[PDB]
Length: 121
Length: 58
Image (cartoon, rainbow over all chains, first blue to last red; front, top):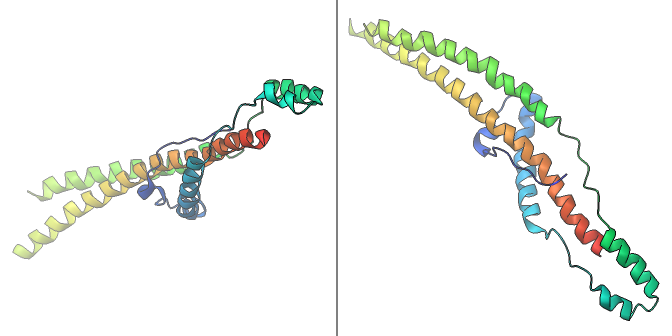
């Protein structure tokens, strides 16, 4: 593909606790951050060929021109990647957050804080 | 008298606090996680486009 970025929020990131994916985050930060700076390095593209010249002193200039036309024409596919199941490996330990403790916590918060007033009396 | 009143006063807010923290935590960490899991994948990607242009040009 190329670079992407979402909600990189490092403190809560590691914090997860779905344990076989909990551990991953702690490393995945550093794998990532190393990653982020390493991209931040490269050039994207290199020069554009001085074809006018390379004909000059590649006087096998059929080769130059062959490769020239090919280079002028030459347009890479883009990379491979595969972990766009992580999008959904998210949604699972995206409902864990939700269900487990979204709802638990509202429920629990209700009785307790409510539970403040009446026993405050 | 005063003992039992302070026992109740502790327990009631306690319960608030700990649940409200438990909610807030999982929301934040995951919505953060949602985007971290991006970022991981996609970094790889931009690298390979960068690399291609050098690689062919060499």
